[PDB]
Image (tube, rainbow over all chains, first blue to last red):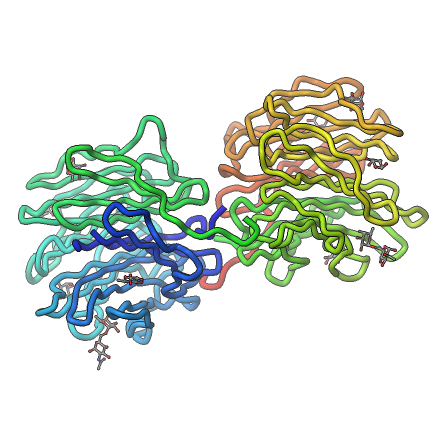
Length: 309
Length: 309
Ligand SMILES: CC(=O)N[C@@H]1[C@@H](O)[C@H](O)[C@@H](CO[C@@H]2O[C@@H](C)[C@@H](O)[C@@H](O)[C@@H]2O)O[C@@H]1O
Ligand SMILES: CC(=O)N[C@@H]1[C@@H](O)[C@H](O)[C@@H](CO[C@@H]2O[C@@H](C)[C@@H](O)[C@@H](O)[C@@H]2O)O[C@@H]1O
Ligand SMILES: C[C@@H]1O[C@@H](O)[C@@H](O)[C@H](O)[C@@H]1O
Ligand SMILES: C[C@@H]1O[C@@H](O)[C@@H](O)[C@H](O)[C@@H]1O
Ligand SMILES: C[C@@H]1O[C@@H](O)[C@@H](O)[C@H](O)[C@@H]1O
Ligand SMILES: C[C@@H]1O[C@@H](O)[C@@H](O)[C@H](O)[C@@H]1O
Ligand SMILES: C[C@@H]1O[C@@H](O)[C@@H](O)[C@H](O)[C@@H]1O
Ligand SMILES: C[C@@H]1O[C@@H](O)[C@@H](O)[C@H](O)[C@@H]1O
Ligand SMILES: C[C@@H]1O[C@@H](O)[C@@H](O)[C@H](O)[C@@H]1O
Ligand SMILES: C[C@@H]1O[C@@H](O)[C@@H](O)[C@H](O)[C@@H]1O
């Protein structure tokens, strides 16, 4: 056995250096980090890798950028009073961030997504966090905004209860948000300049899929992932138009995730992609995309070993 | 969500009064109790119902009898040093029992079973606890004995790694032990008077099934249960001869347990039977046998609600 909480949410980040970090919850409610550099074995995931804490079964999201102080990471979660909360890696240490002090109440079954653009050693970051206030069918998605200070943003959509949410900045100040609407279709909401509008993407999916989204490049390339636990992973790809969604699967390892589990995706470069899932073990696994090979299940991420094992 | 640890072991007891108790592990490693009287709703299962603690994913077993001091319960488990341990309900309170002081080392992946006969308001109890020392294929089952003081008993069998173990006293000082041998057959070891011998029962089963056994009456009646997580429950029945094993299932709720989960059974009277399993939720469920109706899935057993839900 491991210390990975069954039906923990997952969050993941990646940057060119390739450095990856993945966040998950342990049996004690702590948020742990595992790390990978290049194709070296994963490190971390132990009781010595706690970065924060949240209510048990808290949703999670994470973003990263490089700053003059080093690598910045923000991990979003919910506390035991269902208040939207944030842990900060400030380039050298983990601390509690300012978002928790705002008093944003989140629906108990809400998921979280986050995106960032612009942050660098010569420009400030722009963060957007997406959440729901209500658990019921037809609830909207709400946005909280950091472009110097936290303030409320938009609300949009009418969703399945506790919908998955994918969020990606496809270009500077250009946002795409993916969620599952009340007809069980994945839908898309878009910001290009001065307004939100309904996007052209849609796809039928199992009720209650976990959703993730990434993007890169100039077209830009967008990939939207969804998975119901113990069903195969799906990907929709945009390269100027949307393709027909396809399964990412391994005939020798059918539907490798456990029921009622979540996914997370990261990307960096042009292009490295990880899509994390939770399997028997309880284990943290991932799909990996490699140029010239395709998709495969990669190395297992360590998530601790309880005493007596 | 609940506070039921996913892939927790389960132990259950029942006595005529019908009182049931079921034991499971929570996310913090505590052993909790839920209670039922007659067909009234289940009670307990909360953080206020802790009876002991054990290593995370500890095996569990339990027995009960009535004494001059009240209802006696013994719950067997393993501590973080893999030492066989015991919690005592002494008729009025929960305390730590004497077995832990003996120093019986248990294999990390061992299951536990226990039986009792003879204990009453006019006779002392006789307890037997079954465990393994080694995790490997071909390991034996070992017995610890209470008939006034703890001492070692028999060792027998050659098992699948971490085999399920069922144990029942089919009559005064008459014992039947069920386990899965290295050929994946469920086998039977028997004590009637002065020696252990190989029983006539055998049945093919999926590798690694969770096993439970109960018995009652004068024939006697024996029932042996086995289940692999996310497969249907099986029962073999003895009423003078063994039947062909059959599935206990509900066409509207196929294979209702989660992968890699465990079962436990209780019985009392002539005859009431519960077979507990772990399902999505994470929930503690049970099959129930009712004279004139047959088998059905009964009321859900409460297993706590984490803060923020
Ligand atoms: C007056 C004020 O609020 N100043 C803030 C500083 O105290 C703070 O250190 C910085 C950075 O905040 C951290 O990073 C940003 C991007 C958010 O993630 C925030 O929640 C987090 O605390 O911001 C102001 O300068
Ligand atoms: C001298 C000695 O060990 N005496 C024992 C008592 O201290 C003890 O209270 C009783 C009962 O023990 C409890 O119940 C038995 C059936 C076992 O479950 C045991 O492990 C548990 O502590 O036993 C002796 O009289
Ligand atoms: C960017 C930083 O990289 C390593 O120093 C980790 O130990 C930190 O937790 C953080 O992820
Ligand atoms: C990029 C945009 O930034 C602010 O204008 C928000 O109010 C919008 O909703 C959007 O996030
Ligand atoms: C980048 C593209 O932007 C808009 O055209 C959307 O309608 C598309 O679905 C896609 O997100
Ligand atoms: C980066 C890759 O882009 C296209 O080749 C897709 O068909 C793959 O699934 C992957 O997203
Ligand atoms: C036999 C006893 O019954 C009730 O008093 C429960 O509260 C105890 O924990 C025990 O099961
Ligand atoms: C009923 C019998 O009791 C003792 O003799 C033990 O040594 C045996 O193994 C068996 O449990
Ligand atoms: C009660 C019966 O006892 C012996 O005959 C065993 O061989 C049987 O399988 C059964 O346990
Ligand atoms: C008590 C009952 O006995 C027989 O009727 C079996 O066929 C049932 O499955 C049940 O064990």
